[PDB]
Amino acid sequence: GWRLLLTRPDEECAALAASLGEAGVHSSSLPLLAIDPLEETPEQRTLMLDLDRYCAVVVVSKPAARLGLERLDRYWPQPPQQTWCSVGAATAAILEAYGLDVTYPEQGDDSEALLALPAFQDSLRVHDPKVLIMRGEGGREFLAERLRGQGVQVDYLPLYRRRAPDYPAGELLARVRAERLNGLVVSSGQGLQNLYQLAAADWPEIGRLPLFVPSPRVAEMARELGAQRVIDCRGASAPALLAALTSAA
Ligand SMILES: [Cl-]
Ligand SMILES: [Cl-]
């Protein structure tokens, strides 16, 4: 059967490993990014104290929901009236567990899916619309750029930095060989980049394996890097990965 390398951050990695194990798929976890919470600056705290200026808040990732909820809880006994948005169901559920109503697409692989969602566009129907994006220190500029194009002002709240964990030399190749892995999962472009960087000289070998990517954009990024077997899952969730595994080899 399928024997997969997972490369997602540690917390999301364990939840995926468990789902895959429950479905009877073997996996080995090698997080290619670690999540380092950011120290809130005075300018960032001000954004949070003025959270009620935003008609929508977009949470781009599971760590952004977790860390973003900490600051919400810190500064808001009662959350202001605004629309909370997510790209996927899995990010939405962290917010939902807190008690928020979340706007998100059902297909939901990428920023585009949220951007095109009628419920999301409706939340922008406001005088001088302002949106807050909760995310890492860096990321995709697409959503901000597009929102600004429609006359929406866009602020970022960085919550964490993403860094490559330090592994003993050869960890990636050792894992693929020792665990007889026949597939790789990445869940983002940065994750895919870190994989290429860590593969280094063994990339011709590693790039050979079925590479399961969450979206068309990441699929394109992977071809550009020389990955020979690029597989587009319809999103980053476990069910999406299972359906993609069934269809592949
Ligand atoms: Cl992954
Ligand atoms: Cl970052």
Image (cartoon, rainbow, N blue to C red):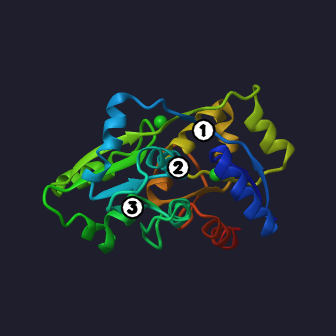
Q: Nearer the viewer, mark 1 or mark 2?
A: 1
Q: Which residue is mark 3?
A: 84
Task: Tell me the distance, in whole angstroms, between the alpha carbons under discs 2 and 3.
Answer: 22 Å
Of callouts 1 and 2, the N-terminal one: 1
x, y (%) of residue 133? Answer: 36, 49
Dot 3: within a 10 Å radius of its alpha carbon, few (fewer than 14), some, or many (20 or more) residues?
A: many
The C terminus: image quadrant: bottom right
Q: Amino acid at mark 1?
A: Leu
Query: Along the line of sight, which residue is nearer the eye, 232 or 106?
Result: 106
Question: Mark 3 near ligand 2 (CB under 8 Å)?
Answer: no
Determine whether, in the image, residue 113 is placed left or right of residue 199. Answer: left
Of callouts 2 and 3, the N-terminal one: 3
Q: Amino acid at mark 3?
A: Trp
Whether residues under marks 1 and 2 lie with C-beta atoms below 8 angstroms apart, the answer is yes
Q: Using the rendered view, name the quadrant where residue 197 is placed.
A: top right
Whether residues under marks 1 and 3 lie with C-beta atoms below 8 angstroms apart, the answer is no
Instruction: Label 1, secondary structure: give it.
Output: loop
Q: Nearer the viewer, mark 1 or mark 3?
A: 3
Q: Amino acid at mark 2?
A: Ser
Disc sitting over residue 33 in the figure: 1
Q: Which residue is mark 2?
A: 188
Whether residues under marks 2 and 3 lie with C-beta atoms below 8 angstroms apart, the answer is no
Report whether residue 14 is seen. yes
Dot 2: within a 10 Å radius of its alpha carbon, few (fewer than 14), some, or many (20 or more) residues?
A: many
Dot 1: within a 10 Å radius of its alpha carbon, few (fewer than 14), some, or many (20 or more) residues?
A: many
